[PDB]
Amino acid sequence: RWCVYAYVRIRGVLVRYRRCW
Amino acid sequence: RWCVYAYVRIRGVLVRYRRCW
């Protein structure tokens, strides 16, 4: 399977993005 | 495929990552 994992963290925030097909 | 994109930053160094299998 194909998936995608993203993780953003700056200042004091954390935006963990994701996705799958 | 496996995509990966993150953007973590601390102190004064931004660790960015980008790549897809």
Image (tube, coloured by chain):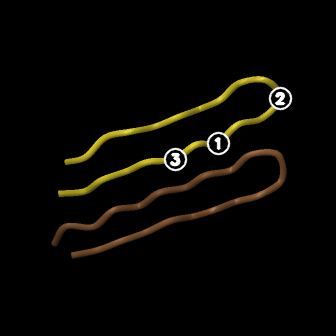
Chain colours: A brown, B yellow
The percent position of residue B1, horizontal first and vertical second, equals 17, 57
Amino acid tagged 1: Val
Chain name for mark 2: B
Q: Let me know if marks 2 and 3 both belong to one chain.
A: yes
Q: Is B21 located above or below residue B17 in the figure?
A: below
Residue drawn at (58%, 43%), measured in percent from left and top? B7
The percent position of residue A15, horizontal first and vertical second, equals 63, 62
Could you tell me if the residues under marks 3 and 1 are in contact, i.e. CB atoms within 8 Å?
yes
Residue drawn at (61%, 52%), measured in percent from left and top? A8
Q: Is A15 located above or below residue B17 in the figure?
A: below
Q: Which residue is mark 3?
A: B6
User: Which quadrant holds the N terminus of chain A?
Assistant: bottom left
User: Which quadrant holds the C terminus of chain A?
Assistant: bottom left
Distance between the alpha carbons at the discs numbered 3 and 1: 6 Å
The percent position of residue B16, horizontal first and vertical second, equals 53, 34
Distance between the alpha carbons at the discs numbered 2 and 3: 17 Å
Residue drawn at (65%, 29%), measured in percent from left and top? B14
Q: Is A20 located above or below residue A15 in the figure?
A: below
Amino acid tagged 2: Arg
Q: Secondary structure at mark 3?
A: strand
Q: Quadrant of residue A2?
A: bottom left
Q: Is residue B5 left or right of residue B15?
A: left
Q: Which residue is mark 1?
A: B8
Q: Is residue B12 left or right of residue B20?
A: right
Q: Let me know if marks 3 and 1 both belong to one chain.
A: yes
Chain name for mark 3: B
Q: Which residue is mark 2?
A: B11
Chain name for mark 1: B
Amino acid tagged 3: Ala
